[PDB]
Image: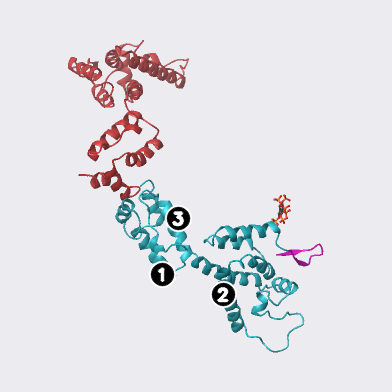
Chain colours: A red, B cyan
Amino acid sequence: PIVQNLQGQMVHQAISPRTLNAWVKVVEEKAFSPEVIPMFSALSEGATPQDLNTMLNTVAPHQAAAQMLKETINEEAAEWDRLHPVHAGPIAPGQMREPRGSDIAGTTSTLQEQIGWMTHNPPIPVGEIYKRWIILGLNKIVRMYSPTSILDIRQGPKEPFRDYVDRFYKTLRAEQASQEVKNWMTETLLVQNANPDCKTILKALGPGATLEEMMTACQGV
Amino acid sequence: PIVQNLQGQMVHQAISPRTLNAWVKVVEEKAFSPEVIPMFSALSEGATPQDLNTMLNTVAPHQAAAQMLKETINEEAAEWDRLHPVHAGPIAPGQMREPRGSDIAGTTSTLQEQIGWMTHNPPIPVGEIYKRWIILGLNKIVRMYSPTSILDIRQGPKEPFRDYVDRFYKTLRAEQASQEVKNWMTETLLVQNANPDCKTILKALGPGATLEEMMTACQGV
Ligand SMILES: O=P(O)(O)O[C@H]1[C@H](OP(=O)(O)O)[C@@H](OP(=O)(O)O)[C@H](OP(=O)(O)O)[C@@H](OP(=O)(O)O)[C@H]1OP(=O)(O)O
C-alpha cells in the first residue's frame, strides 16, 4: 500500500506478515471456493502491483490455477497494449510515461514508478486494474474447481428451505453463467429442484414470487 | 355449391365424390361425437339446399338420429312459415317469390330457384339457414349419444391435468347446458373433480383463477 511519511510524501509500505499469512491460509485451506474472491479483495485493499505479485506467489505451488492466472494476465496485458498503443513522440517533463502491460503487472517497472502512477490528481489506478485482472483469473479458477453442476443441487427431503437456497445460490455464484441464463435458473430451476412439500407450496405461490415470499411460505416445511 | 360459367352466370356444381365420401366416413366412423359438427360445417361449405339433402341421405340408415333431424327440420320449417306469413298479393316481375319452409329445405323447390334465391344483391342465404337447422338437429343427436355425464368426468390419479381438462371441456361441449350453468360448471366442478394433488394446488390458487394459471400450476403434478 501507499502511506505518507512525516514530510507529507507518499511512501510504499509492504503488506504486513499476518495479512500475507491470512492470504496463505485462504489459498491453502479453502480449495478455491467462491469466497476466496471476497477475501482476496479485502486482503489486497489498496495494494500496489508489487504487493499483488507477492500475493500471487502463494498461488504458484498450485500449477493449474497459477497457469490459468498467468494466461488471463497475459491476455489482459496484450489487450491493454492493443487498446493503449504506445504513442511515439515528445512528452511533457511534468508528465510521466505510460506504463505498458508488463509494467502494470509489475514485471519490468519499479516501486517508485507505481507509486507515482497511482499517486496523482487525477489518478490512473494501476492497482485496481491489475486487481480486476487477477479477479477474472480467480473467477475462472473457481469455475474450474467447482464440484457440482447447478443441475445437481437438489433439496433434501428434510433439508430446510433456507439451506437449500444458500447452497443453490453459492453454486450459482461459482458457475457464473450468463445473466439471462442466471435469471432463468433462479426463476425456474430453484422451484423445479425443491422437495415435494416445498414444491407444492411454491407452485401454489405462482410465477413471479419474490425469494422473500418463498422463504416465508416454506419456513418450517 | 355455386360457380360462375364462362359467360359469367351462376351455375350449380355438385359436391365432388371425395367430399361426400369424407362426410360418409365422418358419419359412419365417429359415433356422433362432438367433432362431427365442425367437420360437417367445413364439408358443407357454401352448399345449396339440394346438396344438403345429399349429405342428409348418409344419416338415414341411422334411424334415431335421422328422425331427430327430421323433427328438428319440420319444427324449424313450421316456425319459419309462422314468422314469414305467405303474403297474398301482386309481386314485382323483377322480384322472385318467397320460398316456403318446404322450399328452403329443398323438398318442393328446384335447383334454379335455390341458385336464384342465394345469388342476389342483397342475398337471402337459404343454404346457411337450412345449415343452421341441420346443426341444431346434430347438436341434439350429439347430446343423445353422449356416453358420460359431466358429473362423471374425474381426473385419474396419474392423469395429466391438460388431458383431464380436454376431456372435461369436450364433454361440456357435448352436453350443451345453459350458459350460466356452464359457467358454474367450469368454475366449480372442474376443481371439485380434480385429483388430490392438483386439487390442493387449485384450492391454494384461490377463486377466479384463469384456466391458463391452473394449467401452469399443475403442469407436472
Ligand atoms: O376444391 P376441390 O373440389 O377439392 O378441388 C380439388 C383440387 O382441384 P382444383 O384446385 O384444380 O379445383 C385438387 O387440386 P390440388 O391443388 O390438390 O392439386 C385436385 O387434385 P389434383 O391435383 O390431383 O388435380 C382435386 O382433383 P381430384 O378429384 O382428381 O383428386 C380436386 O377435387 P375435385 O375433383 O373433387 O373437385
The first of marks 3 and 1 along the sequence is 3
Residue at mark 1: B180
Q: Mark 3 to mark 1: distance in Å? A: 20 Å
Residue at mark 2: B72
Q: Mark 2 to mark 1: distance in Å? A: 25 Å
Q: Is residue B125 visible?
A: no
Name the side, left or right, on which B88 lies relative to B37: right
**Residue B4: in magenta span:** yes
Read off the chain for label 1.
B
Asked whether the residues under marks 3 and 2 belong to the same chain, the reply is yes
Q: Mark 3 to mark 2: distance in Å? A: 30 Å
The amino acid on which the numbered mark 2 sits, given as a three-letter code, is Thr
Q: Are marks 2 and 1 in contact (CB under 8 Å)?
A: no
Q: Position of residue A158 (x, y in %)?
A: 22, 38
Residue range in magenta is: B1-13
Q: Secondary structure at mark 1?
A: helix
Name the side, left or right, on which B40 lies relative to A90: right
Q: Are marks 3 and 1 in contact (CB under 8 Å)?
A: no
Q: Secondary structure at mark 3?
A: helix
In this orientation, which residue lies closer to the viewer: B148 or A111?
Answer: B148
Residue at mark 3: B166
For label 2, the crowd category at 10 Å Cα-Cα, with few meaning under 14, some 14 to 19 and many 20 or more, is: some
